[PDB]
Image (cartoon, coloured by chain):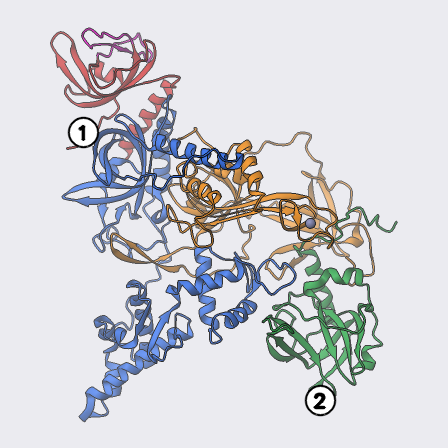
Chain colours: A blue, B red, C green, D orange
């Protein structure tokens, strides 16, 4: 049905996609999985990937790598999978100085009480923050964090009971994501009818494929060969434009397709996604998104403060960063890839801009 | 298998037999006594009323050190005995104190009211 | 066309109008104007090695503007005009050359942006003392005032009991 | 002072922060008013809590795109009411973080019942009281350069993820708050600060929730060990009631860009999604609630 079917690819515009949604366990059992791509689940059009449940343990089985706890929350019961963790490589005790005694005894106190929080018994009150899985028609929760809840007065359980209806009404029973829904309606999908337009679409699909498959670097032929990218590069406009050599259509068309793929990668270069190291591989390209070393070294320009100012100028300017990087890393380092790396790190929050073209960690 | 969920019922709903005998349940009340010789007991509760009993088995699931007059939560099943009537076969039994029982009853009210409001 | 000291780039020629902070001799064929336009320099600003350190101006505050101050080196015919200018004057420069350093005298790589007005009025080089009537001077003074108020820099005059106003 | 105007030492400049009154917004946006020196001393009755009609103010914007107002030769001020005799105990509103993703018509300051997911980074310093640079064990590097005498002060910055069941936000928590963000007793926090004065600086940087320490820091120092273990333990990752400011002043002037692409990888399926930029919140206070675990 037209509104119950998964909108978009369940894109993360809806904020609860990034939340440990506070559902009822019975609603966990009522969820519908996303048929477009499995693994995530739906409630009232909201995409739900993670949940936070509170209840009590009423069943236990221990395996090698995980405990399995049957957790009851009045409305239903579900199995929770909890990975075990050892206190490996713990620190030795010694009659050290007061500071070392402090650190060691504090580390051991923290460890002891973390285990006291983590070790679980039947009848415990339990909280689990995790994600859903379904197998053999069973449905279960994999825990990312879990801990015993100590409550001599039942007040937190009562508060949970009182809370959940209100948050449901305020949020989860809201039947809408209400995005701008900027649907293109597949206009000009079967035929771009223009070589630059087709090149742009090829570049878009190329970056999609590249970051889908986590491609760090590639020879151009390794991307040209992709059957879907070829199924896009084979559109009628380029074929017809190549067909002038009727006696050699294969040669002209293959060369034209190589050319349009080089043009798409050139677009991605000018927009700063891919670059070439000094390696002699004329058609090998590397993607900014994956050069961890470049990130780190850029990060050492302003996490470790810029070394050249004699005054302690908090951060560094974009052009000053760029000159420092070109002198210390690569004189041919493009401004586009540097901008992309900075914006990326800021998305990570490894860097923050203070103002236009000024940055600091 | 996972046991069927022990949904909250008030002592008056077992008193009225509204919860069917043999079904899973969770309920509350002040442990009135502690028959250890027969592992039988009562969990008295009043709600605008005189106190009414709550028979519950207690042979194994928890040899609790708590005492008479303390409040308790019990979860499991209830089943008929000819002399004893319906008696709770507890799967979990735990003590609590200082609990705002009127607010707990209101919380159950809100939960079941939302369940109603939910299609 | 107006262009600000925050916009400058490594190897260029510009106007870069500014307020004059101080002056000094540099050589028989070069002279110093210390200036600012209120905007933040992109590279660390250039500093002139000079024949005597006692410049003209209220140095006891000019040094507090450090990061926004710039040293301008004017060479030949421009000097006899520069030597006459008063402290705090609003000033325009014509075809001021801009030149990035990348190395120092110890052969360490370091970055700072030089500014030069080479000899002769060729390519339009020169200077112009601005009158307070023009909206360009109003804009210069206004940007200075704004940079002073919404400054967010570390406060000087740590001996905060020093002023006593017009005592 | 007196960079262009000759009025040197004309008394110190004065800065007012005022809550606008209007029916156009449910929430009054705060604003800064600067009284530059030729108007000093200010008019009588400009006191906290005084309702004041400001007229003919000069509206101005910084290079950093911050709106602030300033007095001019036509600026005229008129007090409408005196301060109240007793300060009003106004509690901040309580809202779910999803409300702030709605954009406009969402409050500037609020409280939330969130849960700490992970810790990104953590810095501790000891800097000199007279000059903002590091001062290990009181060994000031600026001594004599404006710095008259050596004495040191502690400072701390921490970054958190908080999530409340509806949305996830990056909280930047600073100085005395962090002691509550980590939950240490004042005694233990004091002891920790006192020890770290030996190296004078401690920096940690985490790869993510439950992940290892990043190469900006090292496994060698036991200090780093203790700290890293704490910042990934259920002793920190706990429920709280946060109170925060939205990191950007309440205004319509903010720049804008489309939702970005992010390539998730869940259940071994590649998910490519449009996603919003994360909320950034400045902490105001941290408190435990219901002593929940
Ligand atoms: Zn100092």
The magenta-colored residue range is B32-55
Q: Nearer the viewer, residue A94 or D220?
A: A94
Label 1 marks a residue whose chain is B
Q: Which residue is pictured at 19% across the width and 45% down the height?
A: A134
Against A223, is A120 above or below?
A: above
Q: Sort mark 2 into few (<14), some (14-19) or many (20+) by Cα contacts within 10 Å.
A: few
Judging by the rendered image, the residue that carries numbered circle 2 is C122
Q: Secondary structure at mark 2?
A: helix
- Residue C140 in the image, given as x and y percentages of width and height: 71, 68
Q: Which residue is pictured at 75% across the width and 49% down the height?
A: D148
Q: Secondary structure at mark 1?
A: loop
Q: Residue furthest front?
A: A95
Magenta span contains residue A278: no
The quadrant holding residue A122 is top left
Q: Is residue D11 visible?
A: yes
Q: Which mark is residue B4?
A: 1
Label 2 marks a residue whose chain is C
Q: Which residue is pictured at 39% across the width and 65% down the height?
A: A291
Q: Which residue is pictured at 41% across the width and 46% down the height?
A: D168
- Asked if the residue under mark 2 is in contact with the one under mark 1, i.e. CB atoms within 8 Å, the reply is no
- Residue C101 in the image, given as x and y percentages of width and height: 62, 75
- Residue C34 in the image, given as x and y percentages of width and height: 75, 70
């Amino acid at each position: 049905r037209c509104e119950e079917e998964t909108p978009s690819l369940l894109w993360g515009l809806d904020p609860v996609f990034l939340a440990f949604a506070k559902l009822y366990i019975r609603d966990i059992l009522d969820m519908k999985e996303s048929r477009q791509v499995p693994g995530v689940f739906l409630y009232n059009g909201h995409p739900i990937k993670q949940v936070d449940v509170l209840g009590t343990v009423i069943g236990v089985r221990e395996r090698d790598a995980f405990y399995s706890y049957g957790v009851d929350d009045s409305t239903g019961v579900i199995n929770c999978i909890c990975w075990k963790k050892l206190n490996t490589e713990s620190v030795s005790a010694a009659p050290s100085a007061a500071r070392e005694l402090s650190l060691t005894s504090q580390l051991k106190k923290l460890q002891e009480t973390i285990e006291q929080k983590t070790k679980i018994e039947i009848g415990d009150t339990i909280r689990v923050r995790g994600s859903i899985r379904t197998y053999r028609e069973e449905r279960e929760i994999h825990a990312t964090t879990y801990y015993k809840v100590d409550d001599p007065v039942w007040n937190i359980q009562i508060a949970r009971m009182l809370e959940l209806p209100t948050i449901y009404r305020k949020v989860y029973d809201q039947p809408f994501h209400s995005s701008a829904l900027e649907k293109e309606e597949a206009l000009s999908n079967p035929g771009a009818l223009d070589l630059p337009s087709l090149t742009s679409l090829l570049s878009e699909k190329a970056k999609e494929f590249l970051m889908e498959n986590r491609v760090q670097s590639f020879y151009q032929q390794e991307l040209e060969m992709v059957e879907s990218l070829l199924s896009l590069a084979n559109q009628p406009v380029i074929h017809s434009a190549s067909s002038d050599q009727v006696n050699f259509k294969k040669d002209t068309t293959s060369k034209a397709i190589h050319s349009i793929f080089k043009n798409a990668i050139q677009l991605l270069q000018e927009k700063g996604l891919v670059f070439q190291k000094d390696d002699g591989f004329d058609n090998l390209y590397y993607v900014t998104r994956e050069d961890k070393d470049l990130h780190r070294k850029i990060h050492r320009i302003i996490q470790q403060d810029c070394q050249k100012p004699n005054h302690m100028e908090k951060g560094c300017h974009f052009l000053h960063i760029l000159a420092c990087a070109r002198l210390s890393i690569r004189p041919g380092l493009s401004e586009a890839v540097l901008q992309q790396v900075l914006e990326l790190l800021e998305d990570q929050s490894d860097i923050v801009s203070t103002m236009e073209h000024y940055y600091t960690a | 298998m996972l046991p069927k969920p022990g949904t909250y019922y008030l002592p008056w709903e077992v008193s009225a037999g509204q919860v069917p005998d043999g079904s899973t349940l969770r309920t509350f009340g002040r442990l009135c006594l502690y028959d250890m010789i027969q592992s039988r007991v009562t969990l008295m509760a009043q709600h605008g009323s005189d106190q009414h009993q709550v028979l519950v088995c207690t042979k194994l699931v928890e040899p609790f050190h708590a005492q008479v007059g303390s409040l308790y939560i019990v979860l499991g099943e209830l089943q008929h005995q000819q002399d004893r009537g319906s008696v709770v076969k507890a799967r979990v039994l735990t003590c609590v104190e200082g609990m705002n029982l009127p607010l707990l009853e209101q919380a159950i009210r809100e939960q079941r009211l939302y369940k109603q409001e939910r299609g | 066309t107006l262009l600000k000291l925050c916009d400058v780039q490594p190897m260029q020629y510009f106007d870069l109008t500014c307020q004059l902070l101080g002056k000094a001799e540099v050589d028989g064929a070069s002279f110093l104007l210390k200036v600012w336009d209120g905007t933040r320099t992109p590279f660390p600003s250039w500093r002139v090695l000079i024949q005597d350190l006692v410049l003209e101006g209220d140095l006891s505050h000019i040094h507090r503007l450090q990061n926004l101050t710039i040293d301008i080196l004017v060479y030949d015919n421009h000097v006899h005009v520069a030597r006459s200018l008063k402290v705090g004057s609003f000033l325009r420069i014509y075809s001021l050359h801009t030149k990035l350093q990348s190395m120092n005298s110890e052969n360490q790589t370091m970055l700072s942006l030089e500014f030069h007005l080479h000899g002769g009025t060729s390519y339009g080089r020169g200077i112009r003392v601005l009158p307070e009537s023009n909206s360009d001077v109003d804009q210069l003074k206004k940007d200075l005032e704004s940079a002073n108020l919404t400054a967010n820099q570390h406060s000087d005059v740590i001996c905060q009991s020093e002023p006593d106003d017009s005592f | 002072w007196m960079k262009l105007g000759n009025t040197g030492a004309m008394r110190r400049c004065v800065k007012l922060t005022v809550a606008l009154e209007t029916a156009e917004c449910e929430f009054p946006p705060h604003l800064d008013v600067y009284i530059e020196d030729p108007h000093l001393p200010p008019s009588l009755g400009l006191l906290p809590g005084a309702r004041v009609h400001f007229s003919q103010l000069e509206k101005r914007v910084s290079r950093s795109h911050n709106v602030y107002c300033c007095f001019r030769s036509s600026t005229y001020v008129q007090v409408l009411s005196f301060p109240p005799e007793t300060t009003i105990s106004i509690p901040l509103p309580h809202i779910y973080l999803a409300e702030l993703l709605q954009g406009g018509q969402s409050p500037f300051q609020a409280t939330a019942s969130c849960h700490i997911v992970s810790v990104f980074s953590l810095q501790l310093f000891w800097v000199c009281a007279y000059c903002t640079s590091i001062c290990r064990q009181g060994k000031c590097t600026r001594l004599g350069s404006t710095c008259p005498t050596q004495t040191a002060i502690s400072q701390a910055i921490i970054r958190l993820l908080v999530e409340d069941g509806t949305a996830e936000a990056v909280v930047t928590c600073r100085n005395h708050h962090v002691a509550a963000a980590l939950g240490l007793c004042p005694r233990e926090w004091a002891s920790l600060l006192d020890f770290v004065q030996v190296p004078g600086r401690v920096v940690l940087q985490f790869a993510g929730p439950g992940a290892q320490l990043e190469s900006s820091a090292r496994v060698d120092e036991p200090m780093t060990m203790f700290l890293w273990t704490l910042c990934t333990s259920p002793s920190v990752l706990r429920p709280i009631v946060l109170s925060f400011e939205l990191e950007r002043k309440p205004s319509k002037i903010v720049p804008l860009e489309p939702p970005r692409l992010q390539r998730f990888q869940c259940g071994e399926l590649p998910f490519l999604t449009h996603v919003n930029p994360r909320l950034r919140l400045s902490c105001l206070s941290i408190r435990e609630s219901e002593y929940s675990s």
